[PDB]
Length: 317
Ligand SMILES: [Ca+2]
Ligand SMILES: [Ca+2]
Ligand SMILES: [Cl-]
Ligand code: NA
Image (tube, rainbow, N blue to C red; front, side):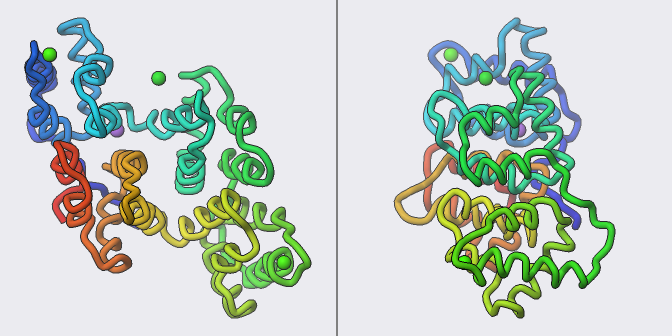
């Protein structure tokens, strides 16, 4: 609906003034992080880029390079994440999930399953113009099996638009998933992909509906029992993403800070990735689901300048 984040444009923005506020608390053996923190988090990504631009035209240095040398810990990755082009961040951490490590598919799934069709083309055409290699090829180059198949299916944003809704297909697909799923001595996860990947959101969101009536089980739990791991993560991702991306991502955070396993990585990207998209929506229904404030969590799970930075990014809920 009306997706709104938290990070808005700073009143009477002064790119040159801020540009050298970072020159200062990046100075000598004084790395003043609370300065950078409050400022960097008080102005939209859009502007902190013309601050990065007014930085090297001013002092001839890379605001990124310099920053990422002076700060350490989760605070470093938080600020770097914060200071980079929005229309180049999703593609960024995608390259940092197909690199010298070669795992971190939790990033692949959560980015490719959550980004709407329109912005997939962005994240993917920009990737090959900044890195040179096909976004699809890099996925197909690491990911294998049905997962990589689904990823490719989702990676080319071709999902049918919201043209209408005909119960005819709704019941048609439902059973197609039903047979591919439950009614079989196996899994034709190829009816799954095409059903989760190609058909529209509206269609699918009501397909998931009557599947519950048809099967007694809801599309998601039938997945858990009919699929395993990574592939399951993707459909699981797509499914709940489809009924509500802010919800999916909202719980993407709960699971990121639960039991002695703070995945600062997800808490970082998920927070910055949509700091100005729908993070407001994220924390407002994070209360109706997880009965907790996203604010209570970040302060009661992390420390350092990290938490107060996250809090100011989180918003004011
Ligand atoms: Ca310094
Ligand atoms: Ca089966
Ligand atoms: Cl890079
Ligand atoms: Na950003």
